[PDB]
Amino acid sequence: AGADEERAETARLSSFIGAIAIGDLVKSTLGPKGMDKILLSSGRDASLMVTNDGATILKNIGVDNPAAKVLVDMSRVQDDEVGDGTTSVTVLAAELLREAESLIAKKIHPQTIIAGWREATKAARQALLNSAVDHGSDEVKFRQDLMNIAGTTLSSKLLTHHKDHFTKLAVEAVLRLKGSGNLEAIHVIKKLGGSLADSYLDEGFLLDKKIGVNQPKRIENAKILIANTGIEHAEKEKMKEKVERILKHGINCFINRQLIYNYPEQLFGAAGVMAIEHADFVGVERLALVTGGEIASTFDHPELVKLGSCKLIEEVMIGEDKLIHFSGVALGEACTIVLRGATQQILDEAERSLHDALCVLAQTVKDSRTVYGGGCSEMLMAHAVTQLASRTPGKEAVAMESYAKALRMLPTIIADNAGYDSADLVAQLRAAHSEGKTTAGLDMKEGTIGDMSVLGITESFQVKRQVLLSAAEAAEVILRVDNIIKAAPR
Amino acid sequence: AGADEERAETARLSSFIGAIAIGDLVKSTLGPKGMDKILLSSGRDASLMVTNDGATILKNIGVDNPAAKVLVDMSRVQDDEVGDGTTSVTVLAAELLREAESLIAKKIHPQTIIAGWREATKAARQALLNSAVDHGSDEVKFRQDLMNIAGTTLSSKLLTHHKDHFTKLAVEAVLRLKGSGNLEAIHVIKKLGGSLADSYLDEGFLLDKKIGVNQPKRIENAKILIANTGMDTDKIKIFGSRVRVDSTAKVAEIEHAEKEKMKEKVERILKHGINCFINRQLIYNYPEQLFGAAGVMAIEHADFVGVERLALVTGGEIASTFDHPELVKLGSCKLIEEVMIGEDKLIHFSGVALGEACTIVLRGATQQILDEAERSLHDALCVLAQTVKDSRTVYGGGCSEMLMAHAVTQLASRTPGKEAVAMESYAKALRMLPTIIADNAGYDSADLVAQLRAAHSEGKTTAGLDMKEGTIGDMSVLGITESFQVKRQVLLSAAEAAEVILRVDNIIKAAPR
Amino acid sequence: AGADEERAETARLSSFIGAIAIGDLVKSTLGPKGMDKILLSSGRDASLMVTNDGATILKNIGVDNPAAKVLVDMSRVQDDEVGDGTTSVTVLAAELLREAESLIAKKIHPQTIIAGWREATKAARQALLNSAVDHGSDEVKFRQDLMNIAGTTLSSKLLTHHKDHFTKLAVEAVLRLKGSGNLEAIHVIKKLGGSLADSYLDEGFLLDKKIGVNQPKRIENAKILIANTGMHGINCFINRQLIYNYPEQLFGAAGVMAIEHADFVGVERLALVTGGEIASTFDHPELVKLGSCKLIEEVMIGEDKLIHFSGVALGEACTIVLRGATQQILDEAERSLHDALCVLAQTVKDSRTVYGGGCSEMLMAHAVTQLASRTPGKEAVAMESYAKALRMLPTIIADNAGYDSADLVAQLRAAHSEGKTTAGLDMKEGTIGDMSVLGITESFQVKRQVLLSAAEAAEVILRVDNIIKAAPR
Amino acid sequence: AGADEERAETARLSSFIGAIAIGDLVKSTLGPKGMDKILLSSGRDASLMVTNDGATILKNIGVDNPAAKVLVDMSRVQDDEVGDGTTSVTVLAAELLREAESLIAKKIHPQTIIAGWREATKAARQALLNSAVDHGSDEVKFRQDLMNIAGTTLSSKLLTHHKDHFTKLAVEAVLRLKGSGNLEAIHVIKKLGGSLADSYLDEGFLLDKKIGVNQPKRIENAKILIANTGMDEKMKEKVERILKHGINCFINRQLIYNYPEQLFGAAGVMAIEHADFVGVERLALVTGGEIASTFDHPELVKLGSCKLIEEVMIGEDKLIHFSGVALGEACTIVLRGATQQILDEAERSLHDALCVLAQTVKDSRTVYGGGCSEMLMAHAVTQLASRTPGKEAVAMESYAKALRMLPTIIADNAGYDSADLVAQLRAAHSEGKTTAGLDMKEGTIGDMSVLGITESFQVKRQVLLSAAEAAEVILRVDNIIKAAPR
Amino acid sequence: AGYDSADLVAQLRAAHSEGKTTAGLDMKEGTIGDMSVLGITESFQVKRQVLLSAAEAAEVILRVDNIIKAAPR
């Protein structure tokens, strides 16, 4: 019995196998003609889920015993500090494993080769302090607001026929957001059709729930109540405490993130108050920043321990469907985007695309710098790294040389998803980068190579800094160790 | 053919096999570029222990039918007076069994052959008076403290590329562990993230827990409170006879009673100046709101083992009921704080008045094998404390071993009779050490043996194996040295351990499946 | 689904296997640490035979059903046109087949893949002018006379402990030989003599034969007679074959020394030196025979007696005798001198070279990587496979050295990309070193012929679409 | 067919197994106390053959695929010149391979290991006179010629009571064998008969053939004719040239034609049908030779001795005798003996004897027997591993321990425990006393000079060089016998 | 011709529908080009006989029953 018991060639292999399975899956996802996947599980799961984003799908399920879940976990921190771009970092880490094949030819000590990872730290610093960046971005900016990185995230999605316009909208959202603190208060939902604009911008948070059939149709000078919490005669007292406190405030709406007792429900309708059952917590937190918030506790909650925004809360209909809109936020820090869309199922993919937009833009505004997208950055660095291996001494250099060829796979994945032959694309791509043009990259729409800058496609500066360091450290854990697993059972 | 039945001569082979099997695992460990082994066992074992110290692992488990357990036990006697540097005693002993093949060739007394062993002594002691030692080791001492043997003990270990720096750190710990205490309370913990320093030295004990997000971040002039019983309340022991109360609302006083429990805790606490509370169990929620406003840091479900070590550090405490604060408690007062240590968040207790309990913090990288820093340090601790006491050392890198081998070769056929084959067997044993040092480095062992033999023969004691070089170099500048008593005891111990097992033969069973 | 038919992937595999099977056995042979193998055959073969050099063994028999015999025949033409060196050309051709697995990845028409060969002309020019060449080989040469290619040829052999000194010596031999006149005429033998020098250059051709116990010891103003058919002041008679007994009595009284069963190879070169012979029937003596008359005698080099021909009037060719420190290693020099001389003859004629120790191979590899990307779609993938082939050569040189191959690849590339053509692989060092200090250089000609020879062998698989049969039953 | 798969450590194992089986069977053979062995083969092998001589049995059968046939074959050439005595060369070569187990422990390269042979260069020279071979064997020798080593060859054999004398005779044969005509001129057949001497020495070659029932009984002032081409106008040409010469005997190495046969009987000339070639070559040196070709061959091209040729009965199995050779350089010995097992052992002994002694007269060098040479060499080689640079050091020390087994095997077959023997033996040789060696009869050590046991110098040079060559080749290659190259 | 098949179909159709008969697939180019410059012109009859024979064979075939296939032989 025991646990693990691995040594020799077999031990290397378990790590090696995990990398290959994940790389093919994520490979489809990258670039303009990315592949959407629907997941079917009948193991304490109810329906097929479709996730374009590679990071979200890896996080959701830990299918088996081999190590890979922890490597996957790290990518999420990256998403909040810079966002998704297109998933590429996981693939590069995996290809590090493949040259281990030439390593059995070493037949002596693999550990000496490990010196390359230390070398990698020198290399990571070589791109972060080198080729990238842009000149401009003074805060807000009339035209430099976007027409950039949002577009590269979009270009990976087909909807960029009318959708590139949607992307333009997203930075209006970031300019309003900045101010007081990070990224959190933004909510996005896609509608089913009817617009050339394909989108609308809302003043406040958008919600979709009802108390019940009975209750007032509409409210005015609405005041908002949020609760963290949901002898027989004493039951009446709960009814009465709620009514007594309620009437003075003029309470127009109540929002609760959970199940709600039947007695109060009745009362709200006669009073002229609309309540919400099991309101999503995420919606509530966004709403709190917007309304000035409150402190959620016991029935002592109504009055000045509560802050209510006073413009207008009503259930309204747009084009055809009926939704409930919270509007008139003094804060301005948090707003909501409602996409009417040009009635197509591509529109149903608007939710897919805007979510990607949400993480990318917040980071883009505070990083204050960017890189050239479309794989422009990867080929340039690849030409340069071939030289780098030759500068170092033979023990360090061999590991460094392998790292350099890793960048080669990205050009193929970007073009292959485009639909143009991958083999042809690599040759022409390398030649333009070699000349010295940073701007030049892969034009997926063309199927060849072109000027990335005209497109407006740029990558956040931060995505490049974090991934280079992360790839090396994860790799080190695997090769230096031939026997591992973890503590506790039996 | 076709069966495992064994008797007399075939029987000898099982004894033979045990010595060869042990040598392969141990050889990787023997020097400046060792590997790292984990070993997980199912059935009455607590977690898999990954050990870089060869002596520790052989003693712990009697794995199988072949007999080698008895040979293993003796190495500990060497440990009691030293037992470390790099593990090499067991390896040489194994080589002795290979010649047993020609022992049948010499047809006579197996035990008279054993008399050769009481010439091993006149070989083992030969290493004594062999190799000038060093002439050093005072008290505390500014530069002779390290950048020596600890580096060699750790040279074998994987972490050597950056860890030789932390190895250097370990002597500072021995400096504060000398004299006035003996050996106690040394606790070392590694962290997942990396820093160039790869280690911080803390003036006291290191723990990992936090009260909650709220509470003052740092405390000063700290008082320590340890409780045998939880902060939880209700039943007590005597129920209270199951309370009545008339209409309902009055019962709110019961709610108020809970407040009183908070009250006693704060009233007694403020006078003492309480900065930190450590409890080895579940903690009731009410006191935390109190602790946060007061400015006191408490620890929920603190581990008991940390507490016992800590008590020696603080001066101890008597743990009882809420009377526990004031005089019955004896908390120390320098600094208790939660310190960002490059990556993870850790809580550090430090500035102990006693000064006899101390902690060293090591980093690493993030791996199951990382936990070998746990045991790398354990031999690092032992090597340095001895280095202070011995004040004597030998040239490392196998310099001592090659010199001795040349001298033993001379003895060979010169001593007539039965003892002649036995004495010569011992002599070629020394040859493997030079081979092993280079093999791990990344250079060809065969070539290394060739060049090394010529330099020692010439008469230069200082010259040895330089792994970074790939060839032979001056060992003294490198700083690699071996403690002096390790050499006197190791050779004696190796011979005696070898004698019992060779003298004991095979495993006995009768039929195939 | 009945009997032996193959399509696409399965048909390809038989071609694939033939190249791989030869490579494992031949790879061992390469390097100072090379190995010699013994083989026993099924038909009309008497016993196990052991051949040190790859070319001799490959040539004798075409055994197996898979195609590979045709590839083998090419190496001998190369040997005649330059020589054995150390066998390595066969290994380079085999490696090109490995890339075919990723070839399927390009996923379309294998035949236009062939247009990559068209691109190989580009690769061929690459092996040209963007390499070290000579930069020095003026005539005689103070330091670079040798310590080079002969040493590398030498290295694969065990004897290179004192032998490397002998190899250096062999260039002195080449300088006198030098010129367009009759390449060959170099013979060397070992002698059970004394230490260190391990070899002495001398006066003339050396031959180990005697007429018989009766006959004069020395001849002056010697006349040389060579006859194709078996049995003037005639001093010496040399015949390449059996000699009839009756004349033997006659020769002793006359004052003439004859040689029975003299080797033909010694004879042909001797003729250029003397001035030629028309070897016919007994009409052969006089003008139809051209003789040289300085001195023919059997002398002891250092102890043992052998026969020396010297004072050639023509002056076109000369011979190095050597000596040595008693062993099989010593007469190995016999094989090595002849090998060292031939490489040099090409070197004088071409007046161009390169740097040895794999210095030439790494530099070219860095440059060829660029070429694949530059060429269009289909051309690019086939062209690059050829380029990666060069990477293995550095590895094979180092692997046989007993030194770490992984470490070696990195450092080798490191010295070459810098722009210093002198740096290369030093096996004796175990790392990388200055090839020029060693003095190793390769002839310019050896690199062009090897490139042409390897390319054609590869195409036998591709120029003909199919070779066997399908389903009779 | 170029494809037999064994990989990694497997290539060594095929080679390793062939040597191990042969060594235990051959080890009991060596020394005065040697063992006789019998073997069975089926499929045209009638019964069990017993061969005292290890070399003879190895040549006869190729039992299985594991490599050993080539190693085995190179014993006969050794035997033809010096070779035999006691078979030890195969035993020593086999033990070299056992250290290959240590080679895996080396963990790097078998070829750099091949520096042992470099070591052999120093070891070969080191032991080729620092052990003090012998200073006698002048050439011819009145009686140091034998009553020594030949007796030792016979010691392992029962025949040593009446056949010890037979052994003495072989050296006389050797003296005539001196010269550059080294390979040929030895023929011995045992004859059934009686006499204490048990042998008769002929002044010429002994053959066993007859023309036919018809033909002259005896030829005097004989002329000898040898023809390369068979006898198969032709009748008359042969008589016409035959008559003038006076031709007394014709020897042909092949089939003879019937027409001449009638003519020879009337003529007075004795002819031999299908005479073996080996006898003929020996005869040419003896008679001054002749140029054998077509029927033109007669007169001057033919030289013929004329002392006497006749067909007679020794006592059993009729033979034809050639005698009175003018040259005197070559002669032939016939052994009679008094019938038993011991007598047929005579055939065994001079096959072994002439070759041992032939080199002994020519070499002028021999070594002390009984293991004396081996122990002294062993002490000397201990110094050597240190003397060489280093790679060549580990390689030297491994070669050195091999010599230790030879003392052990002689003692082992002597009926005494070798441990005491090894220990006591080394001290004597180390001291520097060359004459002292292993005395099996004694059970300890003694002066073998008194015994008269000496080994030829050649047996020691050929064994060390052959062991070197027949080891490097076997370890190196994994493709053994099936079909031709690559 | 070694060139990627899907890309090829796209460029090919746009040029032919364009109205230029001369333009066609250029295998050496790996794209489309002027066939006439190459000098390539299929005999007209080869195109009509193939189409007509296939047509008549088809008439009998999806109006019968007994058959199958293996290969030419």
Image (cartoon, coloured by chain):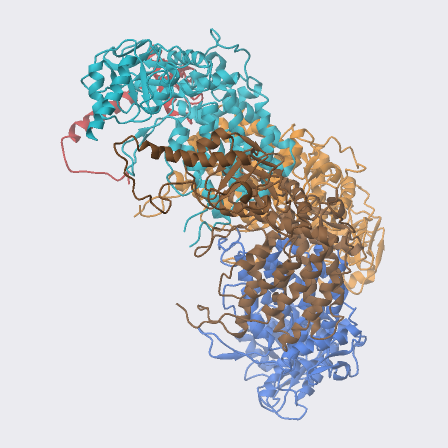
Chain colours: A cyan, B brown, C orange, D blue, E red
Residue C31, position in %: x, y? 64, 46
Q: Give the quarter of the image for residue A333.
A: top left
Q: Residue at x 25, y 23 (%)?
A: E51
Residue A272, position in %: x, y? 23, 13
Spot the residue most to the right.
Answer: C220
| Residue C458 appears in the picture as rendered | no
D440 sits left or right of B13 in the view:
right
- From the viewer's side, name the closer residue of B252 and D100: B252
Q: Residue at x 47, y 6 (%)?
A: A142
Please tell me whether residue A157 is drawn above or below residue C348 in the rendered image.
Answer: above
Please tell me whether residue C295 is drawn above or below residue C315 in the rendered image.
Answer: below
Please tell me whether residue E17 is drawn above or below residue C208 in the rendered image.
Answer: above
Q: Residue at x 65, y 49 (%)?
A: B153
- From the viewer's side, name the closer residue of A316 and B488: A316
Q: Give the quarter of the image for residue D471.
A: bottom right
Residue B30, position in %: x, y? 63, 53
- From the viewer's side, name the closer residue of D35 and C401: C401
Q: Give the quarter of the image for residue A236.
A: top left
- From the viewer's side, name the closer residue of D103 and D253: D103
A94 sits left or right of C173 in the view:
left
Point out the image quarter for the N terminus of chain A. Answer: bottom left
| Residue A236 appears in the picture as rendered | yes
Spot the residue most to the front.
Answer: B246
Please tell me whether residue C98 is drawn above or below residue D292 in the rendered image.
Answer: above
Tally the marks. Answer: 0
Spot the residue most to the bottom.
Answer: D195
Residue E50, position in %: x, y? 26, 24
E66 sits left or right of B475 in the view:
left
